[PDB]
Image (cartoon, coloured by chain):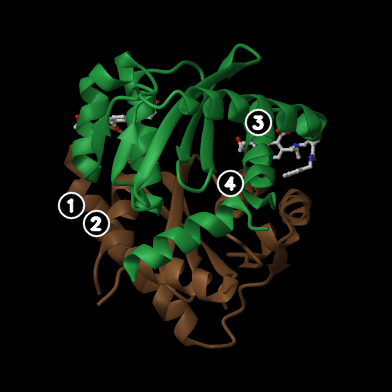
Chain colours: A brown, B green
Amino acid sequence: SPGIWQLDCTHLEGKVILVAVHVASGYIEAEVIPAETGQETAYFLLKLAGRWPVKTVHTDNGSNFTSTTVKAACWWAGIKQEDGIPYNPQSQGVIESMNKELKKIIGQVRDQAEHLKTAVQMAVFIHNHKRKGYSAGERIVDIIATDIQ
Amino acid sequence: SPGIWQLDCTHLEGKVILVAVHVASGYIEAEVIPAETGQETAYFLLKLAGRWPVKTVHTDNGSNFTSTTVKAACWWAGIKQEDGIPYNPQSQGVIESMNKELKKIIGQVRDQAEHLKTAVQMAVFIHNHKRKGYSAGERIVDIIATDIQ
Ligand SMILES: C=CCN(Cc1ccccc1C(=O)NCC1CCCCC1)Cc1ccc2c(c1C(=O)O)OC[C@H](CCC(=O)O)O2
Ligand SMILES: C=CCN(Cc1ccccc1C(=O)NCC1CCCCC1)Cc1ccc2c(c1C(=O)O)OC[C@H](CCC(=O)O)O2
């Protein structure tokens, strides 16, 4: 549970926002990319896993599941690459809601930056700091520290 | 001290590696950029502060200290922007040693990637996971979790 992340891909302004969610806390990392390729996905995972103790990644689609580049990054970084099949139906619902919330935040900050990637990082910041009482940022840290002890 | 970060800029292959160090743990984030500008620095800070609770940043030079774009990012993200004067002489030494260790790791992985940015992320991963017995990644999480509590 402390090591489980879910990948998520959403679209805005003709671009792709690649998101990783720490399932147990709702904490996110995200980046803007021109298109979701194996290489972009692989590079994003490598960044993520150098930053948090990533044990398991549920990939966002079959192409990223299949991709040899993605498997090579998961190999490199010690990540168990898994499918994203929503055996629990509440999963699709949580991600859809997260995408809608993120796009809403992006629209609130959109005039505060020329480039979408700036607005996306502003959105990541607001999302992770939002007290819902703890924030997602507080929850990930507490979950992982408890696991270390 | 759980909220205090230090910026550090180093060079390799005609490129700039921008590093943020969490002072109390030695945990790092890093990126490759064509040149250190106020905009690049500002964007890097915005990313960092959406991901960790960044209270204070000691800027790496006077130009980033002066930069209105950097001050605008620190304002946006709730960061106290401070100078990086090593009133403690051990600080210079700690940073120089980190740069040399990072470059050593980069050379150890350099052949496993075509692009420098990939090798730098592999170096970030190895650095943060290295036990010295706790890793820097374990220390940052424990330090912050204690603080939240
Ligand atoms: C100084 C000019 C830059 N912008 C002026 C601006 C333009 C339009 C609206 C508001 C503002 C504004 O001042 N907002 C306040 C503000 C300032 C700093 C941080 C957060 C908020 C903002 C900005 C900074 C760094 C970036 C950006 C952008 C962008 O406009 O998107 O874009 C990606 C770029 C990528 C890295 C690289 O390529 O260097 O880093
Ligand atoms: C399939 C070709 C890609 N490379 C082949 C390669 C080339 C030379 C040596 C070894 C390997 C190799 O397969 N190493 C194993 C390996 C280790 C860790 C992760 C993946 C693979 C590796 C790579 C992947 C993603 C990237 C990269 C790079 C790069 O070569 O630097 O560069 C930046 C790019 C940025 C995102 C974007 O722009 O798409 O993401």
Q: Are marks 1 and 2 in contact (CB under 8 Å)?
A: yes
Q: Inspect the image, locate mark 3, and give the three-letter code of the amino acid beneath it.
A: Leu
Q: Chain of mark 3?
A: B
- The x and y percentages for residue B34 are 51, 17
Q: CA distance from mark 3 to mark 2?
A: 36 Å
Please give the residue where the numbered disc 3 appears in the rendered image: B102
Instruction: Please give the label number shown on residue A105.
Output: 2
The dot on residue A47 is 4
Q: In which chain is the residue bearing label 4?
A: A
Amino acid carrying label 1: it is: Gln
Distance between the Cα atoms at labels 1 and 2? Answer: 5 Å
Q: Which marked residue is nearer to the observer: mark 4 or mark 2?
A: 4
Q: Is mark 3 within 8 Å of ligand 2?
A: no
Nearer mark to the viewer, of 4 and 3: 3
The residue that disc 1 covers is A108
- Residue A68 higher or lower than B38, as above or below: below
Image-based side of A141 in relation to B118, left or right: left
